Amino acid sequence: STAGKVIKCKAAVLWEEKKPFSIEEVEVAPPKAHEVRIKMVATGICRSDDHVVSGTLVTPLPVIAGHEAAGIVESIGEGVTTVRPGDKVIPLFTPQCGKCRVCKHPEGNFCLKNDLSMPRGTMQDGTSRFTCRGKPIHHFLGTSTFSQYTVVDEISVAKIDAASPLEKVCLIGCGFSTGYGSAVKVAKVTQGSTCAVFGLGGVGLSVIMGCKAAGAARIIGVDINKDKFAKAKEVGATECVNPQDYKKPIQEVLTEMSNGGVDFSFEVIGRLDTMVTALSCCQEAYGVSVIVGVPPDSQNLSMNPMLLLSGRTWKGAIFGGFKSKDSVPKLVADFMAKKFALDPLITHVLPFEKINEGFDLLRSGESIRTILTF
Amino acid sequence: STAGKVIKCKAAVLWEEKKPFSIEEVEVAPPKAHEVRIKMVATGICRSDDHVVSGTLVTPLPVIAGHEAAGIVESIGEGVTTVRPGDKVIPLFTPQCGKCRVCKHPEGNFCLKNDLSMPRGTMQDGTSRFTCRGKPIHHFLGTSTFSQYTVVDEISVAKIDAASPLEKVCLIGCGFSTGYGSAVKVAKVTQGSTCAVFGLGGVGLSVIMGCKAAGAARIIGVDINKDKFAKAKEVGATECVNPQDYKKPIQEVLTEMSNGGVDFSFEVIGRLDTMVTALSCCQEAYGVSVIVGVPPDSQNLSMNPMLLLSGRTWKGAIFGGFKSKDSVPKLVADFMAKKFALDPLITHVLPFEKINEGFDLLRSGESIRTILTF
Ligand SMILES: NC(=O)c1ccc[n+]([C@@H]2O[C@H](COP(=O)([O-])OP(=O)(O)OC[C@H]3O[C@@H](n4cnc5c(N)ncnc54)[C@H](O)[C@@H]3O)[C@@H](O)[C@H]2O)c1
Ligand SMILES: NC(=O)c1ccc[n+]([C@@H]2O[C@H](COP(=O)([O-])OP(=O)(O)OC[C@H]3O[C@@H](n4cnc5c(N)ncnc54)[C@H](O)[C@@H]3O)[C@@H](O)[C@H]2O)c1
Ligand SMILES: [Cu+2]
Ligand SMILES: [Cu+2]
Ligand SMILES: [Zn+2]
Ligand SMILES: [Zn+2]
């Protein structure tokens, strides 16, 4: 029993940008009040973790990154009432404090206690629970799951069903719920509709799964990597287009194909240009475009405001619009009742120590999701 | 008497950008199949008409502009069924052809037969019905109401009540319905909300009548002309701020004032920087911003897509989201039943011949709406 005491264990520390993760011994403090220490069982490699390596997503370094994961409470700090040692849990990179403006609003889910808008890389009380080489290491979006153990605030953890398969439902902590909710909760794809999805990585395939669940009649997947097409058609794409095959720009190609513009489009890559392309190819009078991708830090896009004046709606969302502590238990329960599949998304399962190999698979385009098991 | 013959009459022609309108004698050809010729009774001076003079809104010159008006039908062409001679009608700058994808869709109103996206300045059949010294004069948005008689396509005209005061209700052809529908139909302002309205001209004051009636609790009017403030508080603003009074930028003042951002904002000026300011001052997780102003031709705004990823919605709309032929008779019928006051928007009534004086009152900050009588 490790309770009440510091744990020494391995974590993958990123000491500086554009470097490999370094697997090292770190010391993890015991939880303080309202904090929970979690033994990690599986964590997915998401493209936003790679944005930290490339410097596109700015957060204080050195850092233990990792935010899509599932584990078991090893101990709870003073005052924790929503989880108990031995519970299976999913860390929440968007917290739900339940007490702010946004948590109390019926539609908002970007809680004001998040660490994404102006990242401090600490716990809610402003300190770190990690030491590595005598130095405190930063947390990432209050989750830090590339570690055998991590400590999170109570507003950042959800108890899930005790029979969940943790090496599959860790995708509900990020990729799958982000994609699925952008379609069914943020865009509100309607039955009969034509949808176009830019990007067919794990979030993008999850956006197709949500569009097909909302009853879209046509779901076009767009990617420059044609090897992604078979899995996209497998989860619901009625057709796939690769922009490099055409001589016209893809917004004209899609407008011609949809006879005037799609009803819903989704940018699920993170590029300033495909974000304006995705808005453009939706129908000018009633089209809805949803930005899901994370843009390079401090870069502005350029667009003509007449694209909106005619009637288009442009929205973005974090974590598919779901209030995270309410929604994740319920999405795991739906997965258990076979309402949606997560297995098409998992292409590689590697032990934690091959983290750097899992990232190279993401960078070379060969994986959708790699799950790392501890 | 005139039916079947060319009418020779007075019309305000704009021959060149940045010049006064020229009161000319023009020949108005009679209506071809499915066109209606109208004798004008009251027409308002809207900023979009001034945008043509400015070169802000490109449309083929020479032109008879004018788009906010009401008249009596003088003669119908072969096949008109929705109006007869003697009917009071309001011409529609956004048509409603009934047959396209947008007109069939329940929520879009920007009919594909519009002449606003790439102005042709002709009747639907690609020709002009107006000549002046043997030269064709172009139509403007299929309405051209700065003339004693005009010819419009049947998809661009709505028969209204027989008892309607035509000199109040010409406002429902543009300014009022546009601002009102923007708040109640496009933003769908909620009871208890805080609204911020940038621009307090005729259309902005109608956006404040729409917010107040949707039950908004707080309505912050923003204008650089402090003289517009008293009529904004009379139709409903709770407060008005002037950007030039502050040392810090108006998105910061507004965020500070509304305790983290407003619920709904509207840009009703037509500038690229206030379009981005109005998006920024609305709440980052669940704020809605609606662009109503017409931007300058071919200019692009620059904005940080993180404004949208946190949860904001940005949308624009023409004519306040109203399907024109269906909504303009009901708004008139509702004006009739005292459901809204039109009178605070009319500050000047002048005879048509004093058109150029009515534009210098608009350009000077002195009027909201000047109505020109025939
Ligand atoms: N909004 C959220 O809450 C949230 C959550 C998770 C992930 N994200 C972001 O979503 C985006 C997608 O994440 P992912 O894990 O699915 O990434 P991924 O790398 O697996 O998917 C990207 C897909 O985009 C394709 N792509 C790249 N350039 C393209 C282009 N020019 N045109 C068309 N297709 C292109 C790639 O080939 C790839 O298949 C990332 O930016 C990630 O940071 C946001
Ligand atoms: N979307 C539509 O269908 C549609 C229809 C009609 C009008 N419009 C557009 O709406 C706009 C307003 O029309 P209107 O008739 O109400 O115009 P208006 O000129 O009467 O009002 C513009 C108001 O904005 C104010 N203003 C200008 N610059 C400002 C700034 N920098 N910051 C704050 N306030 C400032 C002016 O002082 C004025 O009160 C125009 O762009 C017009 O083209 C659009
Ligand atoms: Cu992620
Ligand atoms: Cu107008
Ligand atoms: Zn909160
Ligand atoms: Zn139509």
Image (tube, coloured by chain):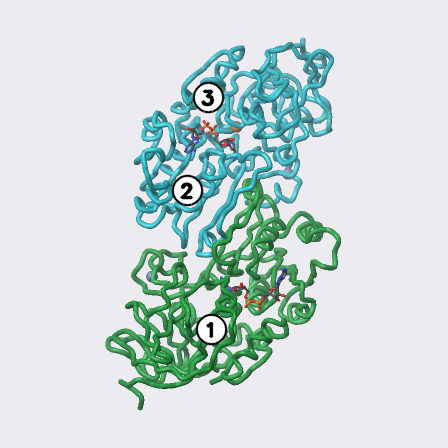
Chain colours: A green, B cyan
User: Which subunit holds the residue at mark 1?
Assistant: A
Q: Are marks 2 and 3 in contact (CB under 8 Å)?
A: no
Residue in front for this viewpoint, B156 or A209: A209
**Numbered tag placed on residue B362 in the rendering:** 3
Q: Are marks 3 and 1 in contact (CB under 8 Å)?
A: no
**Numbered tag placed on residue B265 in the rendering:** 2
Q: Is residue A333 visible from the viewing direction of this image? A: no
Q: Mark 2 and mark 1, same subunit?
A: no
> Mark 1 = which residue?
A68
Which amino acid, mark 1? Glu
Which amino acid, mark 3? Leu
SS for callout 2: strand
User: Which subunit holds the residue at mark 3?
Assistant: B
Which amino acid, mark 2? Ser
- The residue under the point 50% across, 16% down is B372
| Location of residue B151 by image quarter | top right
Whole-number angstrom distance, CA of label 3 to CA of label 1: 57 Å
Residue B145: horizontal and vertical position, in percent?
A: 58, 20
- The residue under the point 37% across, 35% down is B222
